[PDB]
Structures are given as C-alpha cells and as structure tokens.
Image (cartoon, rainbow, N blue to C red; front, side):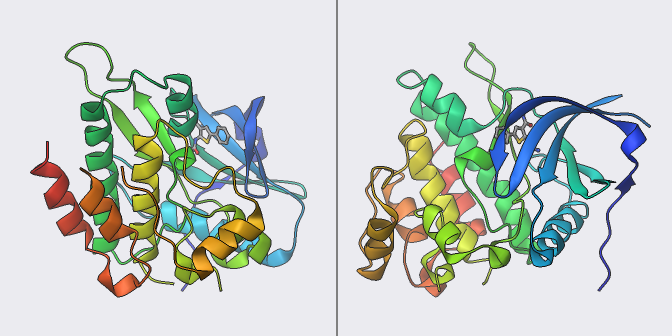
Length: 261
Ligand SMILES: NC(=O)Nc1sc(-c2ccccc2)cc1C(N)=O
C-alpha cells in the first residue's frame, strides 16, 4: 500500500469565501489553476492520526470515478495546513437545499435522487470500498431538476476525515446516519447511512432524532429502537436493520428503486 493523490502547490490555488465547517475542517470556495472552480477543505490543527485519515480519504477518492461521485483534485499543503481540493458542485449540500425548499420537492424527484445515490454506492460496493459518511450534507446538487422536463443530478462528496480517527463523542453526533456497529467496519455501514439518508431526504432535510441529546441518541441505539417509516418503507427498514449481514446489497437496493420509478 502507498497512497495515490495529486499534490497541489499553494501557488495553484486561490482561497475565496467560507462555506461552512465539516468534521475538523473549514470549507471554502476556491480556484484551481494548472482555472477550475473548486472547494478547499482546510483540516484543523490536530492529532497526526486525523491528518493520516484525511490523506487516506483523498487517496481513496482520487482512485474512483463515477457520474455521481464528486471529484477530488488533490491535496495542497500550505505550511502547517492540509487542504483537500474538491469539486465545486453548483447548488451545494442537499440537506440545506431541502430545508429551504421544504414543502415543494415532489416524491418523484426524491426517487431519482435516491436511484443516483444507490448507483454511486453500488459501484463502491463492487470495488469493496467503504464511504463511511453517507448523509444529505455529503450529497451535492449539480442540477435542480425542478423545472418541467429537467431532472435533478446529485454527486456524493468525499467522506472527509475517516470514521476510525474520530472521538466516540463525534460518532454519537452522527446518529442516525452512523451505523450502529460503528458506535463501539464493512461496506455494510453504507447501507445504514443510505437508509438514514433516504429518511432525511423524505422529510425534506430533517433527519430523525434531531431534537435528542447525545445521551438519548446513544440510548436509542443501545435499546435498538426502530427508526421511523417514510413506500420506500420496506427498503429503508431493510437498510436500517441493526444486524449488518441482513441489509440488502446495493444491487438489490438499486433494482428495487428502478422497478419503483
Ligand atoms: N466536494 C465538496 O464537498 N463540495 C462541497 S462541500 C460544501 C460544503 C461543506 C460544508 C458546509 C457547507 C458546504 C459545499 C460544496 C460544494 N458546493 O461543492
């Protein structure tokens, strides 16, 4: 093993406006010259394992292609700062967009988005690679598709700092997207995240257990409580099965989403 990713020189990037924060990151709009519109993910000063995890994600995402996976252009080191350089996708995070468009996103639109997500994720399953952070915030909207005769187009972004390097406190915050087996490893975890993401999508960007304290989210998992029903219901319940070996394959998930729309 030896990572593979493009090294970007600090001269080749321009840092523009702050977009928000990811896990141990600050995220900015930028420009990449040899000019590409890009996103810059500046890793906070942090333990070395966080840094290694960041690089492991850049390497992973630098070696996969898909219609519905966002590009990773490289990594730029700017003195003590490590910066992942990624695709700017026009309309930003899906969760933010859904909350703003709450009430007038039709179920048929959500079905297309779901089918796109599933096919991205079936490709990673085929490659036996784990994403580890499927949630609406990591789904970026390239086309709105709300206009008559158009259809939406999403891209799944990089998972950022790997799950294994995060604190237990951080993993709790990711409930219900976090697979229960990860609270105390496989491609199975993304079936849970997918399920949790489908609920998030069905509820116009509100995910379940958002009004719950960390202790309550933990307790929900400990008592293996069942998450609400969106009929994507069968599918979502299948994905949101605590036992990883009972979650259906993306081949099945995708075949099912097709013969639904
Ligand atoms: N590749 C990638 O992740 N692109 C991202 S991340 C992001 C973002 C992240 C955290 C808070 C708010 C926005 C926006 C965009 C974008 N518009 O493409």
